[PDB]
Image (cartoon, rainbow over all chains, first blue to last red; front, side):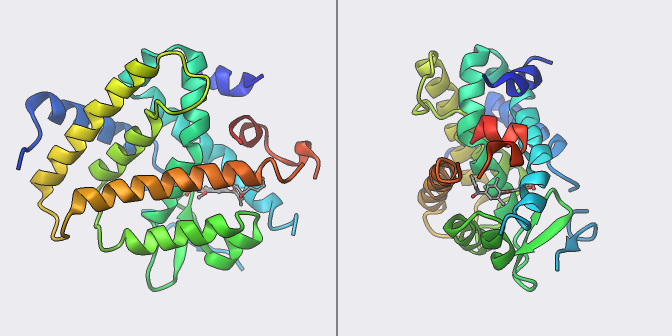
Length: 11
Length: 229
Ligand SMILES: COc1nc(C(=O)NCC(=O)O)c(O)c2ccc(Oc3c(C)cc(C(=O)c4ccccc4)cc3C)cc12
């Protein structure tokens, strides 16, 4: 759930 | 009329620098290439992923954004991508070719975007760009509009609602105080810019309603595009 968007949010 | 305070100038340096660092090209007009219904719609959805990423990059360069929990960051970014990407294209309207520029490289016509799935929203983005000509928005004004849309407390599921609303109120003063200082030769420039924020907010909601419409297998759509809607 929003895992790429989360990966990019954290560096 | 009140002009930017010393701390408001720092906030303007910061948010302006964020914007310029994450804005495609900036030449965008001379690296521009003109383009000559799930087949125009591939070759657009394909070009979104870098544009969404540039928005994430803007938000991550804003120290106020980075103080929020990532649940709230995800929520904020999900609500302001299409707004920011729409503003970023509308400020790149060429009155003579009657095109918008995406990724600072591809010139598109009103028809091309409506044909690529934007539907009525492409009419809204072009109309905005046309009206943003007489406004003569600079990089600081665009960056501050972007920060105002990002720090929307109204977005559903947020935790730090009042912290976000405080960040947004900091940008709105700095932006108004900058507006007072830039002395634009338009009457009631602030009231009219505030109406434009609302035009953009309407673009972000209509686009996010045409998504729920196309469900056309989801895997034909880029991964980032699906996480933002
Ligand atoms: C203004 O929008 C955009 N702005 C910029 C841009 O200027 N970037 C900023 C900068 O210059 O730095 C872009 O690069 C864009 C690239 C692709 C794009 O593609 C879309 C999108 C996103 C949504 C729809 C739908 O309506 C829809 C259809 C089905 C389901 C849901 C939604 C259709 C298309 C073609 C829209 C872009």
